[PDB]
Amino acid sequence: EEPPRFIKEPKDQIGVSGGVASFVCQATGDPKPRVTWNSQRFETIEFDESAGAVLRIQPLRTPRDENVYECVAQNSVGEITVHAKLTVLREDQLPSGFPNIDMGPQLKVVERTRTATMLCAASGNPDPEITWFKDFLPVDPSASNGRIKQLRSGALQIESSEETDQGKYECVATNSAGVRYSSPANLYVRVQNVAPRFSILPMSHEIMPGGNVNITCVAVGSPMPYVKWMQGAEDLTPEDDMPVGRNVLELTDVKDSANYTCVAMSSLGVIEAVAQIT
Amino acid sequence: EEPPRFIKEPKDQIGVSGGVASFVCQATGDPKPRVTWNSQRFETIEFDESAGAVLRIQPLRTPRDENVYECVAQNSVGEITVHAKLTVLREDQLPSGFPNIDMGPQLKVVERTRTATMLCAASGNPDPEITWFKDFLPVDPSASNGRIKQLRSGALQIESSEETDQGKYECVATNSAGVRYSSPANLYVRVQNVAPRFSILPMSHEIMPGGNVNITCVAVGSPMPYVKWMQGAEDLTPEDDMPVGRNVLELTDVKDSANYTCVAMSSLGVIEAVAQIT
Ligand SMILES: *[C@@H]1O[C@H](CO)[C@@H](O)[C@H](O)[C@H]1NC(C)=O
Ligand SMILES: *[C@@H]1O[C@H](CO)[C@@H](O)[C@H](O)[C@H]1NC(C)=O
Ligand SMILES: *[C@@H]1O[C@H](CO)[C@@H](O)[C@H](O)[C@H]1NC(C)=O
Ligand SMILES: *[C@@H]1O[C@H](CO)[C@@H](O)[C@H](O)[C@H]1NC(C)=O
Ligand SMILES: [Cl-]
Ligand SMILES: [Cl-]
Ligand SMILES: [Cl-]
Ligand SMILES: [Cl-]
Ligand SMILES: [Cl-]
Ligand SMILES: [Cl-]
Ligand SMILES: [Cl-]
Ligand SMILES: [Cl-]
């Protein structure tokens, strides 16, 4: 038995109409505490097995949202309260130094293990402090053990991208004038894990001496396989330029019968299919 | 002015007929030395701006190849000689403990920056020492500053694969009985660097109320782009399963006119094309 205490408490906020405001609040204890905040535009997002909670108001409408909000915490021992004030202005009423997003993040795809750098440039007076959110919850780069870090520019740099880094990112600029949210941007993390297989097999043929036949080989997969030709030991396709996906063996003037082999190959496998001219 | 001296000298060798034998020899000095070894099956391969040289005999034929070979080194100051003996046996005359390749390396494709591990398991008595060759020249893992290293198994592990790691690899087993070469294996290093573009554009249409039309979007590139649909702000394709390459928007019973947008997207770009139903 032990009463709960807040690891993080909510701060007061000054928002802009049409934009977003978020209030964060989590606590720890034994047994675990359960946090609660107290409408279509209001939404709650839990974390840390319910012990954390984020209130998100979007879009902001003034002065209806302009109130105080409490974050309670239930426990077998007791419960505590924490306050946080919301203010909301309109675009035509924003102070000169209110934060503005000059360049926000944008829809991006990153292949697994590669680096994703979610850009964000913001002005204001004083210069705003950039935080980031992902799936309506704040990003904590310090928790990543060096893999994720914010650059001096505000950019969120995600090295060694993994599947869980996929999600809806938005950069947030805060200063004494208030808080401005960017247009959201989805990050997609691409895994390429499909072994190569033939889509169009080479056809066997019978021909007269010269004797013009093209033989087509088409293979698919993710990554997309190279496709080269061989007649037994000797390979016809030169390495310098080897086709990906599709390779059509043009035979000009043929005299004797021979068996041609198509090899499709990627990092996930090698496949073979034979075409025999008679 | 300074005479030349050998950084590495050739060793005597015992080969097997049909197989390969290689003699290595390089030297250093001011001015630089130029090394020379002294037939269709004989070949020389230079390195270190000609100061290094490798004699390669393949295939071995006994007893015609069974001779002494010298590696001279020309220089303004003088020149030096180094000897090395070749012996060649037939398969039916191999000592019990002569090296054998149990599992050799094989044709492989590795994507750039990924790890390529060229396997090689060999038996013999005593147990043979594995060295590796690439494009008829020996691999020196110590030169890679940790990126390349031989495993205890004999495997050549190539981390952070780059374009120059592409080439023809063969593992070599050596012990007191002699030297055995494996079947060669090509390693291909795949770079995926083609920005996404549409191969089949969506078609505009005119329809009656219900009004069944499928709209096809096909894009290509390396890596291969995702392909999703949107009607302005709202995106129709669910994230969980998003098609790669091809996406065909089935419209069942339509009543009002609307503009549908196809977005193709990879790590190298985002492209858009619109289809308008009337
Ligand atoms: C094969 O393809 C080439 C290139 O398109 C063409 O010029 C040739 O006529 C074709 N020959 C056939 C189909 O026999
Ligand atoms: C090709 O292979 C087939 C099937 O094994 C065999 O029957 C045929 O003799 C071969 N033809 C040629 C020209 O090598
Ligand atoms: C569109 O494709 C689906 C699936 O193949 C098919 O069942 C349907 O009849 C098609 N409708 C069209 C072409 O209008
Ligand atoms: C679709 O866009 C075209 C081209 O901008 C525009 O002329 C048309 O009014 C739009 N139609 C609909 C249904 O939104
Ligand atoms: Cl807060
Ligand atoms: Cl900052
Ligand atoms: Cl923005
Ligand atoms: Cl297949
Ligand atoms: Cl040697
Ligand atoms: Cl070893
Ligand atoms: Cl082998
Ligand atoms: Cl295009």
Image (tube, coloured by chain):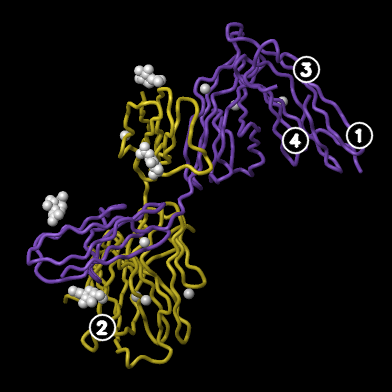
Chain colours: A yellow, B purple
Instruction: Name the amino acid, label 3.
Output: Val
Q: Does the closest atom of ligand 9 sit within 8 Å of the Cβ of label 4? A: no
**Residue at mark 2 to residue at mark 1: CA–CA distance:** 93 Å
The residue that appears at 65% across and 36% down in the rendered structure is B140
Q: Earlier in the sequence, mark 3 or mark 1?
A: 3
Direction from residue A54 to residue B269 in the image, left or right? right
Q: How many C-alpha atoms fall within 10 Å of the one at disc 4: few (<14), some, or many (≥20)?
A: many
Residue displayed at 33% across by 71% down: A184
Q: For the point 36% across and 70% down, which residue is it?
A: A170
Q: Are marks 3 and 2 in contact (CB under 8 Å)?
A: no
> Viewed as shown, does residue A234 lie left or right of B262?
right
The residue carrying mark 3 has its beta carbon less than 8 Å from ligand 9: no
A61 vs A199: above or below: below
For residue A68, which numbered disc appears in the image? 2
Q: Chain of mark 4?
A: B
SS category of the residue bearing label 4: strand
Residue at x 35%, y 55% (from the top left corner): B225
Q: Are marks 2 and 1 on the same chain?
A: no
Residue type of the residue flagged with mark 4 = Gly
Closest to the observer: A163 or A55? A163
Label 3: which secondary element: strand
- Name the residue that disc number 4 marks: B52
Residue found farthest to the front: A209
